[PDB]
Amino acid sequence: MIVLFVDFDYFYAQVEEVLNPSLKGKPVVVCVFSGAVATANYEARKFGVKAGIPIVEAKKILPNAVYLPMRKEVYQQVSSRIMNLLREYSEKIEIASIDEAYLDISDKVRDYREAYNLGLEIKNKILEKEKITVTVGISKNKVFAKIAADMAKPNGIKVIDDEEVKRLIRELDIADVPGIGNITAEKLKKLGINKLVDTLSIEFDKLKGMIGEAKAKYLISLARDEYNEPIRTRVRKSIGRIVTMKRNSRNLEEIKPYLFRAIEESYYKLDKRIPKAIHVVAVTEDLDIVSRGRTFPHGISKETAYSESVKLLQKILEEDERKIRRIGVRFSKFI
Amino acid sequence: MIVLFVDFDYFYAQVEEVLNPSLKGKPVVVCVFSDSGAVATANYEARKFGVKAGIPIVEAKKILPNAVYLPMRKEVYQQVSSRIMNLLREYSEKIEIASIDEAYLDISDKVRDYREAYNLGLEIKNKILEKEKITVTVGISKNKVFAKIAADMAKPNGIKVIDDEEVKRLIRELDIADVPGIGNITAEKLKKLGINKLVDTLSIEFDKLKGMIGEAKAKYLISLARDEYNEPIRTRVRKSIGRIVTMKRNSRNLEEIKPYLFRAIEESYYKLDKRIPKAIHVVAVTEDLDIVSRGRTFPHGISKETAYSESVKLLQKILEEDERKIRRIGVRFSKFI
């Protein structure tokens, strides 16, 4: 297995320097507003300005900085484009967060050298189309790919071969393990567990009564080099849309525009796929849910969806006396 | 099949004299206002002075300008109609509420002949009279159209059976304009082609009639004249019971969605009455107003607490497999016993 992990360097602060390019070199800190620090760039992170410290402690440390409010949805749109460009590179992708993604590339590359070169082409593509630099980590599982990027950041790329994994197992501090908090690691330090190998010299049940069962199996499985968590690529089983009407209605020719608008948004919100089932969904005046559907053994063209949704909505009006408040469509069973 | 049709005589006008008994013999008309509007229903006594239902009000203010005029008390009429329809479901499992004052009942499996249908129809008239002080008209025949025809000839406060033998006679002798679903203009188009009775529709070719009366009524008329018009009584039954609630803010924290989700369970189980579902579905409306849904089926019944615990883990599966923020959350229950 070959995992490729992509992490966007100080994402929030980096997006701010893209849209306003005057903040080069100057320390930039994004904050949630009295408040807390959301993200700081490398320039400000070098002086102990981390994420999670209060704003006024950060303005003690460096008053001559640029402080920006949290523009969360600005940063989400850039992230959405970059994730879309990563999906372009391999089908098996897991979006872990707004600035983290895991790619399974076992079928695209044969070794770590080709994986390294593929990560180089990913970094340049992201830099070409969004002017964002990233850190790429490559290893044998998700955890070690993340460890790789933590060691190479910022603007880095690092492979961790299988022999460096066995070295890191004996040498990496427990605190440096992804998915493990700082207080859980402080509890392990106080009991004699400092390195990842130290979990091999303790009984499973004893460690379980210490940090819980989820973390106990997590730590032991990594120390054993038997951590095999797959890339969880999310697939939409159904694609649809529900739209609210201006008034509650039972007139078919008034509901049809809203129902047809839901089709247009839904049919063209799954790239290259055709459905075999259509479901019309009505939310009644009392906010109940009534729905009727049909399955076609062949595909449902968009025009078929037009004439079939009307017959399904007609079937809803005949079998229910309540007025309809919102109307929508759901597509499923893709081929 | 034996259909039993019930029609409330001048309902809006009659229910009003139930609440005010001083209108004995006094002409009363109920009107819908929309400046002014039109007359909704008129009673027996005003109906004899050229004041009928459907025509404006001030048109009535030259023909009967000193009779009682009353505004629309729609909510009272609706509540009276609903009790009567509920009283009717006691008599028949299959019923179709066609409008505020008309309901069809299929009683084929409750009576054996038309004489027993007559006795059942008479006791229905006397139960509606004793519990709501409303007189109704009853029509009994083999389908909806002839059950209504029977009522239209027996009204008001009437009960009439139309034998299988009088159906065939009415096909030959009943005027075309008296057929439900067609009006004067369409009936006039037929009278000048040679079509004056229902039986005359069979005695000339299809597609000439079809290309002059419209197609939908062409097959309707011929269906009746062949006495193979057997459209069943469309009884409405609620497949599923549920509720979807809007949240004040889009979120993805299970602990914050849980209250809204639990509210939708409490409302659903109060609307179930003495019903117990075997299937539960959690429905989530995401921020882009997409629908994500997951369900479970239980061979036995679903408690209210199972629903509490099963909805949480269903919402967990939704949150587990969809990255979008949740805007609305709800439950629905199906597969009743």
Image: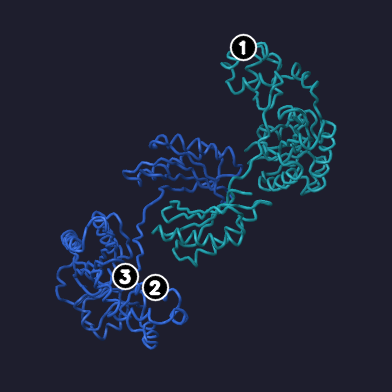
Chain colours: A cyan, B blue
Q: What's the residue type where badge 1 is placed?
A: Glu
Residue under the point 57% across and 58% down: A262
Viewer-proximal residue, A250 or B190? B190
Q: Which structural element holds mark 2?
A: helix
- Mark 1 and mark 2: Cα distance apart in space: 83 Å
Rendered image: mark on residue B145: 3
The quarter of the picture where residue A305 lies is: bottom right
- The tag earlier along the polypeptide, 2 or 3, is 3
**Residue A312: where, in percent of width, then height?**
49, 58
Image quadrant occupied by the C terminus of chain B? top left
Q: Circle 1 sits on which residue?
A: A203
Q: Are marks 1 and 3 on the same chain?
A: no
Q: How many marks?
A: 3
Residue under the point 60% across and 62% down: A303
Q: Are marks 2 and 3 on the same chain?
A: yes
- Determine the chain carrying the residue at label 2: B
